[PDB]
Length: 138
Ligand SMILES: OC[C@H]1O[C@@H](S[C@@H]2O[C@H](CO)[C@H](O)[C@H](O)[C@H]2O)[C@H](O)[C@@H](O)[C@H]1O
Ligand SMILES: [Cl-]
Image 1 (spheres, helix red, strand yellow):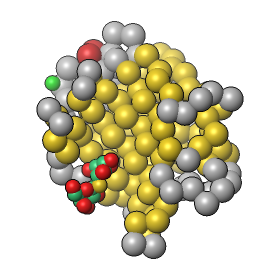
Image 2 (cartoon, rainbow, N blue to C red; image 1 turned 60 degrees about the vertical axis):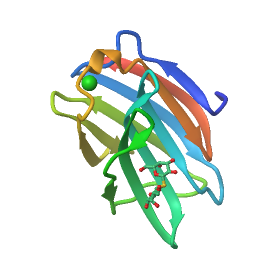
Image 3 (cartoon, protein in one colour; image 1 turned 90 degrees about the vertical axis):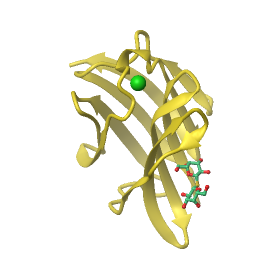
């Protein structure tokens, strides 16, 4: 049972065929989860479940460059549920991050940050009991 906020080092950044796995359970009455795939201060890929945005449940994806958020990409499909165990798999592909939750495809996020091998940390935060975070080359 890891401590959130949690930092996972990604040694040598990311690369296509890299599969990052995050296992956890959403706390009861949750408000947010965040994954932050960081190139130093920058956030190459921010993935942000919000359980109550104007009484809607939304996933917000974005990039942060020199302290500025870009154009959000919003996803209607919301596979998370308060109180339940989840698995998030982030596969790096040549042209995007591909995200599946609970073995079901969720979304893709085109790479805006190009220096993938400098995206050397994944921050995991929000209303979760974090069980495990690891990566594998597939
Ligand atoms: O873009 C991701 C970040 O979103 C903001 S919340 C964000 O704020 C702007 C105003 O600055 C607009 O209201 C947007 O509608 C709203 O989504 C969060 O504070 C960050 O943590 C990122 O999640
Ligand atoms: Cl870049």
